[PDB]
Length: 16
Length: 16
Ligand SMILES: [K+]
Ligand SMILES: [K+]
Ligand SMILES: [K+]
Image 1 (spheres, rainbow over the protein chains, first blue to last red):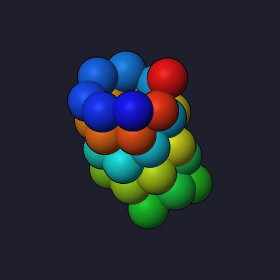
Image 2 (cartoon, rainbow over the protein chains, first blue to last red; image 1 turned 60 degrees about the vertical axis):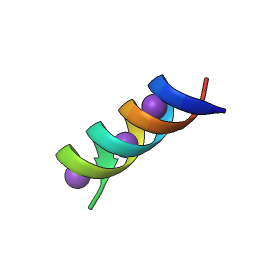
Image 3 (spheres, rainbow over the protein chains, first blue to last red; image 1 turned 135 degrees about the vertical axis):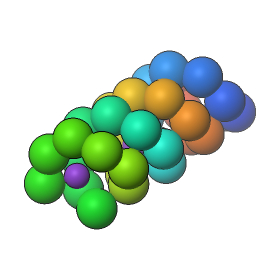
Image 4 (cartoon, rainbow over the protein chains, first blue to last red; image 1 turned 30 degrees about the vertical axis):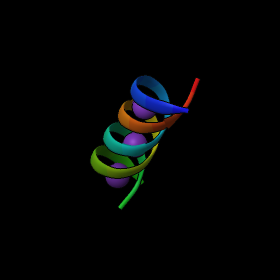
């Protein structure tokens, strides 16, 4: 849990 | 739904 790549909030593919 | 900012796969804070 923290910052980097995977899932959660930020930049990439999913929902606005 | 698609690319840009929000929730889902990619970079920023969460899990992975
Ligand atoms: K992430
Ligand atoms: K999106
Ligand atoms: K995201």
